[PDB]
Amino acid sequence: GATAVSEWTEYKTADGKTYYYNNRTEESTWEKPQELK
């Protein structure tokens, strides 16, 4: 139940959903982060 962007940032793409980007690893995944679950 993590609130507020911690390490990850999500943007909603014209595909109609949000993708999660981790600012340390520079990784973009559609899977919900552990530190943002």
Image (spheres, rainbow, N blue to C red):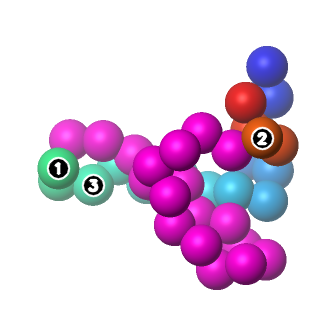
Q: Secondary structure at mark 1?
A: loop
Image position of 3 (left or right of 15):
right
Q: CA distance from mark 1 to mark 3?
A: 5 Å
Residue of label 3: 13
Q: CA distance from mark 2 to mark 3?
A: 21 Å
Residue of label 1: 15
Looking at the rendered structure, the kind of residue marked 1 is Asp
Q: CA distance from mark 1 to mark 2?
A: 23 Å
Looking at the rendered structure, the kind of residue marked 2 is Gln
Residue of label 2: 34
Q: Dots 1 and 2: beta carbons under 8 Å? A: no
Specify the quadrant that holds the N terminus: top right
**Residue occupying image coordinates x 73% and y 30%:** 37
Looking at the rendered structure, the kind of residue marked 3 is Thr
Of pointers 1 and 2, the one earlier in the residue sequence: 1
In the image, residue 16 sits, relative to residue 9, either above or below, namely above
Q: Secondary structure at mark 2?
A: helix
The residues colored magenta run: 16-33
Residue found at the far left of this picture:
15
Q: Dots 1 and 3: beta carbons under 8 Å? A: yes
Image position of 15 (left or right of 20):
left
Image position of 16 (left or right of 12):
left
Between marks 1 and 2 in the image, the one whose residue lies nearer the viewer = 2
Residue 20 position in % (x across, y down): 54, 54
Of pointers 2 and 3, the one earlier in the residue sequence: 3
